[PDB]
Length: 165
Image (cartoon, rainbow, N blue to C red; front, top):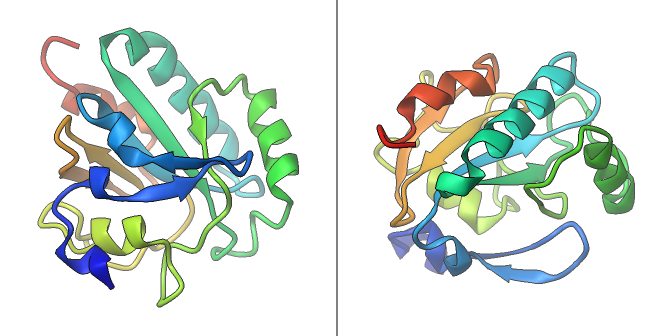
């Protein structure tokens, strides 16, 4: 449980959707949106399309997006990593797709256990991720700066990006 004493997203690693181990310190210096995704939710389309739009408009200013598939919410991400990769490609995703994980419970990926206990990572009701497409905004130092619920369209994050983005 070394995740509990971490102070930055940059202290974690995660397998990408192709199986390559990513050291998240590669995001040092970048503003990041971290989100749990699913292919079989009613808002799947609006979330993917808006995240792609944010990335197209702000990648050159240093925005990065880390999408973590998760099957814990209505069994709405049942497919294999290869299937999910091809699904995201259908929305023209060019940001970073990760291998499927859990976000709640003791088996949750340590990055997610950590984000949920940060001062700005707590939800409106409590810490647990409530459904697909929760979003966390992470600053260039790897700290959580804001959390957005499943009903928040990604475009709501845009105003919270740095004023010179």
